[PDB]
Image (cartoon, rainbow over all chains, first blue to last red; front, side, top):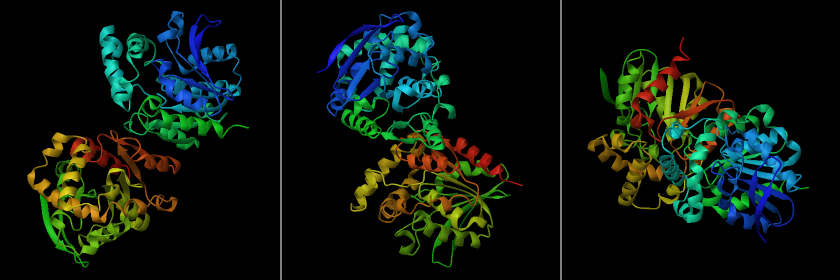
Length: 263
Length: 263
């Protein structure tokens, strides 16, 4: 059964989290928008394949908004990893298979690099390494405008607008409030903090992906870096949100990829 | 000064070709549509930097229509390379910097692999290694349908529909006649014959590119291969036709890339 609730960690964050299943641990880290309801559908699919799946809203986002200012400002992959570690310690998850897109992907990599003992295998998807043109001045306009622009951008990069709309009104209302916060703390600090250096990439197994429909230039360095480092790299259908656009295919990938590292 | 001409080579092909400038040779091999008029603007731009630029319509296409059927059936990069070598001998171009997209890129690689003495440096763009979904059965369709389908596909993937439209009605009238020809002879045999083996890639300098706006999956294999093989890889603005969509950026890429291997 899916359990849903809150837990407050020693850093002051009141986390909203969800769990389902039993078996080896799989952790699903949201993308920058910090909304874990995006994992609902695939979560059931992955859990039913023999894994305990854990997901959560990110600090200051959505239902995890009751968190100290510090937890949502000047965000890096390493900063978020530190908070995730704390959360995992509280939930007693010693080792796991970790997924993450965008800033979630940065966190995955930071975990692979600085907390190898806790990662069975990392699945990063579209690691931000450069700040995209369309988001250069996102923080320069009114909050309401940010919400509107980001709402349109996210939909456009959803990979399936119908499924994006189908996330529901409750999710979209939460996203509306996350957009400005995200813009102030993420886009400028996340990309330069990408742990994509050679010394970050070889302690644990990594399976890297990029969206099949995502314009080549956006995550082009992701591919090149992976290939050069001899790390498995491929695409997933969709764009920025494979777990929303193609939940079945997304679940299958996580299951198969994690299943191969089990022993 | 732009010279335009026709010349019949010993294989029976009546080629149509154009040339401009003086200096080291630059050859612009068209894409699968074999329409060299798409290189019009950039041709002058390249030429003005001290290069003799040569382009031509491809066998069976457009103004090089008068050609033996064999020359546009069961087409591979290697078959095209052969025909092009003969033409180069006939125009007395000994060594050249060669650009090519799609099947033109397959041709470039074949030239780099089999006729290395004739290539100063190769510039392949979007080498087909797989056949996309859409063209999976466009060879069992019919001439009017194909021209309707392909004309839209190309516009879509043009990278700039205004510029594509601005090519003119003569151009599109010729393209109209080529679509089916292209379809019966290219799609099924070009991708499987891609000269992207280890042995094909290290005899001469190669600078590989992919479209910046092209969906990642399409030429994902190109990136992985280049990176794995230590070959320079990057993006160019646009999609499939950077010479049409972004003439100045294209011309700059070609000139700068070529200048690297001069003197």
